[PDB]
Amino acid sequence: RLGVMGGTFDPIHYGHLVAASEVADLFDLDEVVFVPSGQPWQKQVSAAEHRYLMTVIATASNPRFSVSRVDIDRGGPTYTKDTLADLHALHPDSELYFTTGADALASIMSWQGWEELFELARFVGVSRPGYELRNEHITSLLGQLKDALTLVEIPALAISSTDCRQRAEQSRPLWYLMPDGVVQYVSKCRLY
């Protein structure tokens, strides 16, 4: 059992890392591969290497986390379908569990095949405390498909990349929202 964590990580923060650990405890995953996403699907975010290196810095110290550049190296916006194909090729031993934010998930289903996407992995959306499903396509999708698609509330996902981005812009402290390495990387590279 191998977790797959997409995707933007701009910046990565404790919420993401809490979500990875929770979802691994739940589902008894042996490892979690973080996959920073490629180009955006609308033609403004940080450079792929910045997001990759932030993700590597944040996860380095965890024995059961890794970072893959499968989406980064591919070029273009990249389909989730390919992520899993590439990650199935390198981990043929394990069944995959793709996991991502609730809103990001509702943008993958949702422009791609889904029917063929659920053949490749079980799906585990992670959501902030106050989450209410408003997307009716997903509500419909749910009736179709135990347990192809789960949602797991993560209190820590109250912390968001958008807030961290606004806080860095406003020179407001990012301390304790993310590892010291990430905050200082964000600061040094003046990412926002």
Image (spheres, helix red, strand yellow):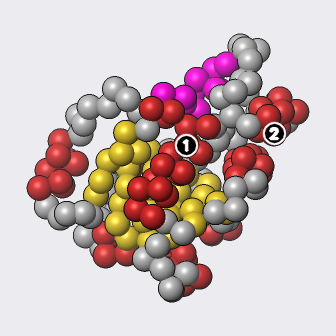
Left or right side of 181 for 86 = left
Q: Nearer the viewer, residue 79 or 154?
A: 154
Give the labeled residue for mark 1.
Answer: 18
Q: Which kind of residue does numbered mark 2 sit on?
A: Gly
Q: Nearer the viewer, residue 135 or 176?
A: 176
Q: Is residue 79 magenta?
A: no
Give the labeled residue for mark 2.
Answer: 181
Left or right side of 176 for 86 = left
Q: Nearer the viewer, residue 69 or 151?
A: 151
Q: Is residue 166 magenta?
A: yes
Residue 119 at least partly seen: yes
The secondary structure type at the circle numbered 1 is helix
- Residue depicted at x 19% and y 63%: 146
Tell me residue 95's x, y (percent).
43, 77
Q: Which contiguous range is marked in magenta?
A: 158-168
Tell me residue 178's x, y (percent).
69, 34
Tell me residue 142's x, y (percent).
17, 54
Pointers 1 and 2 in contact (CB under 8 A)? no
Q: Earlier in the sequence, mark 1 or mark 2?
A: 1
Picture layout, residue 155 above or below residue 105? above
Q: Which kind of residue does numbered mark 1 sit on?
A: Val
- Decide: few, some or many residues near mark 1? Use Cα within 10 Å; few <14, some 14-19, many ≥20: some
